[PDB]
Image (spheres, coloured by chain):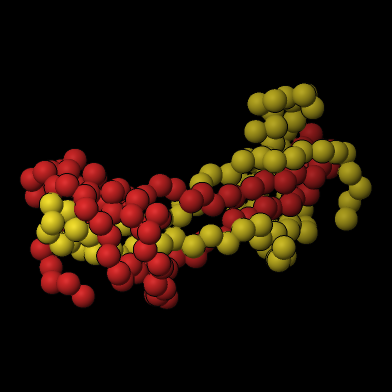
Chain colours: A yellow, B red
Amino acid sequence: GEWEIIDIGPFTQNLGKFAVDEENKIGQYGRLTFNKVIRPCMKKTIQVVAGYEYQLYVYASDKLFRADISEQVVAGGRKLLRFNGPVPPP
Amino acid sequence: GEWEIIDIGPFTQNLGKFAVDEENKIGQYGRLTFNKVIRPCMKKTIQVVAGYEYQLYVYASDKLFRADISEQVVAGGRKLLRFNGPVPPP
């Protein structure tokens, strides 16, 4: 639950474009036209996941082997979670 | 690059089954028959990735909204990386 303000501009301005698009795909606020993302833009840490590489000694056909197995963690894509409004300026 | 021994048994024994199967699917050690995973079974941390939830103030159709956007991180599946041998007992 750690928080962090990120400065506006390119990245956040494309988060707003993203947010408006995916909202229009449900559409039941009508058809919205993206304008701008204003301060403050907040970033909450909701998880920390570790990727692992297992190293095993394995008997197969009663021969011994060294196998390495990854359990990689993937940064997936952006998904719009909530979209409510209108709201007062912060 | 942090290391950790994990005790053998169910989980590691299924990592060895996994490792032998996915090896047979390239097959060019022939056809191997899984027997057992022995100590020590090692676990290396190869990454730490955080999932995020962005909270934005967005003007759309000159109305202000509160949008929340997740950038979830996914624990993907196991992939056999390397498989060499035979080797001496450790």
- The answer to whether residue A36 is seen in the rendering is no
- Residue A27: x and y in percent read 72, 24
- Residue B7: x and y in percent read 40, 67
Residue drawn at the location 88% of the way across and 55% of the way down: A90
Front-most of residues B52 and B44 = B44
Residue A14 horizontal side relative to residue B26, left or right? right
Residue B9 horizontal side relative to residue B86, left or right? right
Residue at the farthest right position: A88
Residue A20 horizontal side relative to residue B37, left or right? right
Front-most of residues B3 and B48 = B3
| Residue B50, picture quadrant | bottom right
- Residue B26: x and y in percent read 15, 43
- The answer to whether residue B75 is seen in the rendering is yes
Figure check: A82 above or below B13: above
Residue drawn at the location 33% of the way across and 67% of the way down: B41
Residue B73 horizontal side relative to residue A31, left or right? left
Figure check: B25 above or below B74: above
Figure check: A58 above or below A27: below
Front-most of residues A89 and B76 = B76
Front-most of residues B77 and B65 = B77
Location of the C terminus of chain B (image quadrant):
bottom left
- Residue B86: x and y in percent read 10, 63
Residue drawn at the location 58% of the way across and 49% of the way down: B72
Residue drawn at the location 80% of the way across and 45% of the way down: B66
Location of the N terminus of chain B (image quadrant):
bottom left
